Image (cartoon, helix red, strand yellow):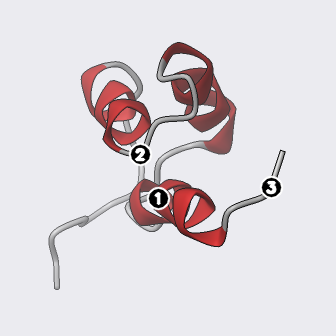
Amino acid sequence: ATASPQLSSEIENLMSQGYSYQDIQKALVIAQNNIEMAKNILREFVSISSPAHVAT
């Protein structure tokens, strides 16, 4: 319950990096909708095809 904007913003954090929402939601199920545990799982697991991430 309670769609918290900040926790959802956590998704947006790695989302902005190019990460895929399919695996993002996947990260949430293992991370029990955690902040860092989800963004960390994407880092650990799924990869990004988007070119130039740290180009800013």
Q: Which residue is mark 1?
A: 10
Please, what is the three-letter code of the amino acid marked with disc 2? Ile
* Mark 2 or mark 3, whichever is nearer to me: 3
- Disc 3 marks a residue whose amino acid type is Thr
Residue 26: which numbered mark, if any? none
Quadrant containing the C terminus is bottom left
The residue that mark 3 highlights is 2
CA separation, marks 2 and 3? 15 Å
* Type of amino acid under label 1: Glu
Identify the image quadrant of residue 7. Answer: bottom right
Please give the residue where the numbered disc 2 appears in the rendered image.
35
Q: Locate residue 34, reporting x and y percent.
A: 46, 36
Q: In this orientation, which residue lies closer to the viewer: 53 or 14?
A: 14
Determine whether label 2 and label 1 are within 8 Å by CB. Answer: yes
Residue 50, horizontal then vertical, whole percent: 41, 56
Q: What is the number of callouts on the image?
A: 3
Q: Which one is earlier in the sequence, the residue at label 2 or at label 1?
A: 1
**How crowded is the residue under tag 1: few (<14 C-alpha within 10 Å), some, or many (20+)?**
some
Q: Is residue 9 above or below residue 43?
A: below
For mark 2, give the secondary structure. Answer: loop
Give the residue at the far bottom of this rendering. 56
Q: Secondary structure at mark 3?
A: loop
> Looking at the image, is 29 positioned above or below residue 28?
above
